[PDB]
Image (cartoon, rainbow over all chains, first blue to last red; front, side, top):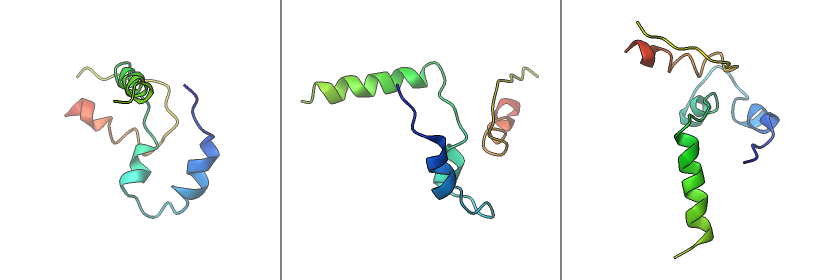
Length: 50
Length: 23
């Protein structure tokens, strides 16, 4: 599982640090052991569509 | 008590969830 470049969210999601929002909180969060297992459970259902 | 700590670089956004270990 490949993360994107970390300079993408740093020039366009947290450009102004005076404010916060719903997106600007979630960037500083890491997946747990089971919340990564749900991402593995997402991509199984994208490959077998119906 | 019972607090945990890991390697984090988000100074604001992860310590919000650190009080969730307190509460």
